[PDB]
Amino acid sequence: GEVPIGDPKELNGMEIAAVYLQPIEMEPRGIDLAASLADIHLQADIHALKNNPNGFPEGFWMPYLTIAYELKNTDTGAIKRGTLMPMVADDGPHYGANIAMEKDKKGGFGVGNYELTFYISNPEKQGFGRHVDEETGVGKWFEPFKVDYKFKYTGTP
Amino acid sequence: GEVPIGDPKELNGMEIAAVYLQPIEMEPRGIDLAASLADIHLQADIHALKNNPNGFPEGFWMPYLTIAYELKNTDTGAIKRGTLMPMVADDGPHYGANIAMEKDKKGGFGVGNYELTFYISNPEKQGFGRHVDEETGVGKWFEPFKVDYKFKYTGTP
Ligand SMILES: [Cu+2]
Ligand SMILES: [Cu+2]
């Protein structure tokens, strides 16, 4: 099952929500941390708001974003970071990564209170274009930004 | 303004339509042929159908596809090849490219009868991931395939 992380944020034309669930199995193999080595799949759910200023229809998935995460256990002080990769599951596309929590050898990533940050950059960083003509053009992309959430990690689903 | 190319195809859980319009100014500069040097913008509209076998909800843009094209004037024999690149306009994301027709340097790309082929590969070729576990996984991706259109080019819209 999915566990929502905090409240979603609306900014820069997008609704940005965080969820975690049980480790998943992703193809192609060898990119994402193997399910066997993980305790959660962390997921960023990011879709266009109404009147998205970059032309994305409401509710469309926001593609080609560059997304990193920072996860901090505030009880122990442990911090880890990584990237969320684009992929598709039965409920649609998202950005995600399997993460070791209890299993992390370094330790300190167990049940407890957590702060999560997403660091997001616009699709142009990956070569995604935008029309700028009068007839069909759209507005400028957002500058790099972050969003912050707090949640209680209750253990690997 | 917008000119439909042949008839849409419905394969591999996607609707695959082709259109052309006037040349467009796109950012970032340099990725694509400058509108100055082009006569059309060639565009592929590819969205998920109902019950898409790869987890995309109905109507969602299909992202991370590799779309090569081959455009042949069957009257003159002129042939040119390229790739459509992902981008967004005020009505949503698509894959497109500016193309010189009357302005082409070798010539033979004027008004007349044309054959257009799209060579399409699945998102995994660009590293887009897919859940395969039982609870959240989706079906395998289509093998690379081609779609063919026949149309009359009447000049820049
Ligand atoms: Cu995932
Ligand atoms: Cu375009």
Image (tube, coloured by chain):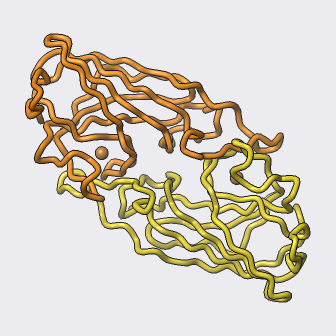
Chain colours: A orange, B yellow
Q: Which residue is more in the foreground, A39 or B61? A: A39
Find residue B85 and report its horizontal and vertical position in percent: 62, 56
Q: Which residue is more in the foreground, B31 or A136? A: B31
Find residue B11 and report its horizontal and vertical position in percent: 49, 73
| Relative height, residue A13 to residue B55 (above, below) | above
| Relative height, residue B75 to residue A75 (above, below) | below
Find residue B92 and report its horizontal and vertical position in percent: 63, 46
Q: Residue at x 78, y 64 (%)?
A: B99
Left-right relation of B117 to A33: right
Find residue A132 and report its horizontal and vertical position in percent: 76, 40
The quarter of the image holding the N terminus of chain A is top left
The quarter of the image holding the C terminus of chain A is top left
| Relative height, residue A155 to residue B57 (above, below) | above
Q: Residue at x 42, y 34 (%)?
A: A67
- Determine which quarter of the picture holds residue B115: bottom right
Find the residue positioned furthest to the top. A75
- Determine which quarter of the picture holds residue B138: bottom left
| Relative height, residue B69 to residue B79 (above, below) | above
Left-right relation of B113 to A83: right
Left-right relation of B6 to A113: right
Q: How many marks?
A: 0
Left-right relation of A72 to A155: right
Q: Residue at x 29, y 28 (%)?
A: A81
- Determine which quarter of the picture holds residue A143: top right
Q: Residue at x 31, y 51 (%)?
A: A89
